[PDB]
Image: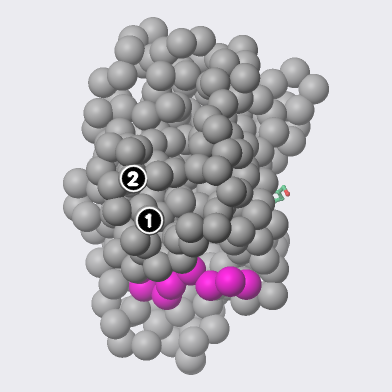
Amino acid sequence: GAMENFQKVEKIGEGTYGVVYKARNKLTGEVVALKKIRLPSTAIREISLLKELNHPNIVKLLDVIHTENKLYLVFEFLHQDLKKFMDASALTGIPLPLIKSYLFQLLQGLAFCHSHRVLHRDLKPQNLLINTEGAIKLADFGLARAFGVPVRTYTHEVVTLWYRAPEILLGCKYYSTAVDIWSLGCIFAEMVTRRALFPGDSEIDQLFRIFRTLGTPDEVVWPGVTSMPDYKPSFPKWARQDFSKVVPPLDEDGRSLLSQMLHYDPNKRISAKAALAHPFFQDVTKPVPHL
Ligand SMILES: OCc1ccn(-c2ccc(Nc3cc4nc(OC5CCNCC5)ccc4cn3)c(F)c2)n1
């Protein structure tokens, strides 16, 4: 069949929807990352369109193969993920110029996809892939619109809530591009501090962690919040903390940017385009990482 063209080399990992292998294309000679999803007509159309969603900071979708009750997604191969790099950099920290380069690149990736009205909806360090040159790329872009974001993965692993926007947690059915800015803000904070910003272990724990740092949202900061489906007037009313406490020793340009990425109101939250123009990026460079 179709899959006799790919030689499996090694197992990379386990995604939300299926297993990912390093593989060799026998006809072209290319080394690829092959995602195998066990199987929907609408999903096939939506995923096939992602072959056109091409940008240097988006993991290249080389092909989509629907065969034998399975969907194979053939991706470009990269060295490792940001999670491994952050774990490896725990003692010393990722240098600020490299954090800045990576955030700048990821914002370009978001600005591109958002310009075509495609959301990621499940950004997290495991979906950010790096090479030895200094590039970083977003993996799994567009798969959430095709399949949804489940509670558990295909292996029953808990899908993390740590990067989930508060509008999603409060039960908004209609997600804007702002949900990805929220997630990337949380990732930015984690790179700087070497600890997850909001490591919640349930929906309410996630919400209350957000509230304990940013203040419990009300009608002043977020018009309509008190009418949202999963909003309860019984939520405790926590005061907002200073960003100087949350992400030390990050400078005022970095804190300004982060604060705008974590605005409660999706309509007030900074866009990817606007974030690229932020003064934080005035001295941005492209360093080569220690991998
Ligand atoms: O524990 C440390 C360790 C062990 C092995 N590695 C590791 C080896 C190779 C790669 N390269 C890679 C992986 C990809 N993965 C994709 O999909 C998954 C992304 C996350 N969400 C689920 C789907 C898509 C395209 C990919 C392209 N290259 C790597 F990233 C890590 N790291």
The image quadrant that residue 194 belongs to is: top right
Q: Identify the residue under disc 1.
A: 226
Q: Do tag 1 and tag 2 residues touch (Cβ < 8 Å)?
A: yes
Which coloring applies here? Answer: one colour
Place of residue 270 in the rendered image (x, y in percent of width and height, measured from the top left): 30, 33
**Magenta-drawn segment:** 143-152
Place of residue 138 in the rendered image (x, y in percent of width and height, measured from the top left): 44, 46
Marker disc for residue 291: none
Secondary structure found at label 1: helix
Whether label 2 lies within 8 Å of ligand 1 gets the answer no
| Residue at (28, 37) in percent of width and height | 268
Query: With respect to residue 236, does 36 lie above or below?
Result: below
Q: Identify the residue under disc 2.
A: 219
In the depicted view, which residue is nearer to us: 258 or 263?
263
Query: With respect to residue 176, does 7 lie above or below?
Result: below
| Residue at (42, 75) in percent of width and height | 147
Q: What is the tally of numbered marks visible in this picture? A: 2
For the residue marked with disc 2, what is the amino acid? Glu
